Image (spheres, coloured by chain):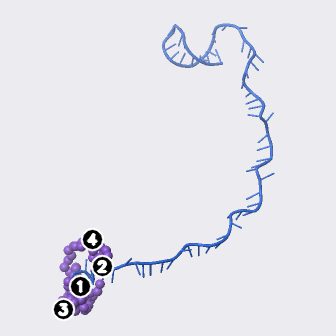
Chain colours: A purple, B blue
Amino acid sequence: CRQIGGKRGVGFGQVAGFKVEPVAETDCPWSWRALPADADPRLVTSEHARCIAAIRGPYWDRTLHVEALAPTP
RNA sequence: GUGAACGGUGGAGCAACACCUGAAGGAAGGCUUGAUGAGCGUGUUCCCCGCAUACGCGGGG
């Protein structure tokens, strides 16, 4: 990976570096994420709200958007 | 398939016009380039100082 974010053709968001480290099971919430509407209520927090959003793959593909429980950036 | 992928902040524009740094102000008042140094006396063994180490050398009044 060289760049992150959008508009990478104009040189934006060039990644200086990254580190990948293990963390405890209860310490990391991976659920801050576009989740389906029938998701587990343990996984759903107060930040997650219903929207027309992709939960997978090409997140820009409006034909693949579903009724999702997603948080807000 | 990083809600991505695609996308020029561009084109034009006088800092410039006018405007006297200088009007006035004493380098003055005293002062031998001539002085100084360049010529006129003593008539024979006697005190001190060093090198030596006394055989004598050097100096000194």
Instruction: Where is residue B60? Give x, y as percent.
Output: 62, 19
The chain to which mark 3 is attached is A
The chain to which mark 4 is attached is A
Q: Earlier in the sequence, mark 3 or mark 4?
A: 4
Who's the residue at 22% across and 80% down the image?
A: A28
Who's the residue at 26% across and 87% down the image?
A: A71
Nearest to the eye among marks 3 and 4: give it. Answer: 4
Q: Which residue is mark 1?
A: A59
Q: Amino acid at mark 2?
A: Lys
Q: Which SS class for mark 1? A: loop
Front-most of residues B23 and B61: B23
Instruction: Where is residue B16? Give x, y as percent.
Output: 59, 72
Nearest to the eye among marks 3 and 2: give it. Answer: 2
Cα distance between the residues tagged 4 and 1: 24 Å
Instruction: Where is residue A61? Give x, y as percent.
Output: 23, 87
Q: Earlier in the sequence, mark 2 or mark 4?
A: 2
Cα distance between the residues tagged 2 and 1: 15 Å
Q: Amino acid at mark 1?
A: Tyr
Q: Residues within 10 Å of mark 1 (few under 14, many from 20)?
A: few
| Circles 3 and 2 on the same subunit | yes
For the residues bearing labels 2 and 1, Cβ distance under 8 angstroms: no
Quadrant in the picture for the N terminus of chain A? bottom left
Q: Amino acid at mark 3?
A: Asp
Q: Which residue is mark 2?
A: A7
Q: Residues within 10 Å of mark 2 (few under 14, many from 20)?
A: few
| Circles 2 and 4 on the same subunit | yes
Q: Which residue is mark 4?
A: A17
